Image 1: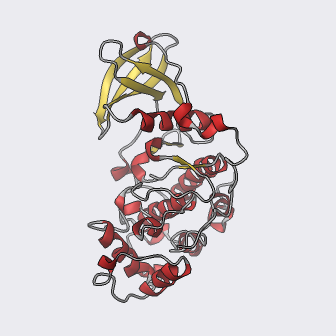
Image 2: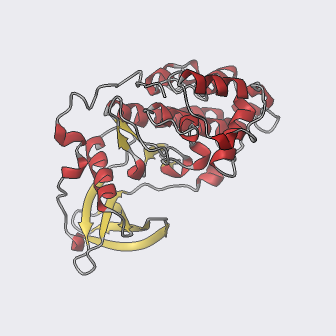
Image 3: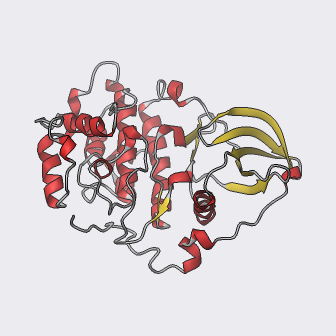
Length: 326
């Protein structure tokens, strides 16, 4: 396996004090439990129950995430990432961190954002709406990459949209990591439909560009109205359905370039496939969302070679966003 480096923000953490990325030695400063009053449940998560609440101290609208017991190392990482990124554009802000003195169980308190069900939301988005919100997610990603942090779970579930106020937040940093040039990460880190080829072929020296693939998947679902775009049945099958769109030739070039040991179990399932034109996924029900610049932007995000992909700031430059600059 040939080593790899991020083309941007390569050395952010290299020139940052230990205290910035050494989340393990980070000490949490707790708030008061009794400062918060629960109002409504917002639904079950896999690792937390989420409640609508109010800070009775200053009457601020809050959301509290009551955590299920999980390894504390993981939550310390999330907290330190949240703290390092606070104030950033379209980054959810951690307001406070509290603990229940009777049950010991911790809970994270975030700013309230009024979220619309994304399933019904993408169904009504205008051409401008896709560009605008895409430009907003980009803001959060460039910011967080510039702070030496990969999100690693970019997907519609983790994007809070308040449509009436056209306000967007990137949430759920529980999988996020600090980028260190040369470091090998574990690849079991995204949601299936949003995993980058680098994860699926078990290439460990990845970077911020992973998020840009995921953001690519989101764009493909929005402009084509096919959510999710790559609907694989498992990790192996996920690559196959990517290969069915991007082609097997560029996939094999990708492994060769990085001297990747492709899992022997891929031998009978990949086959041969050609690069499809993006205009093939265009029909009369989604046509109004698709423009030449949209298809160019997408093609420059969905590529096997993670180094080839547009960086977040390079993506903000694209023709596709020329109207959303006002």
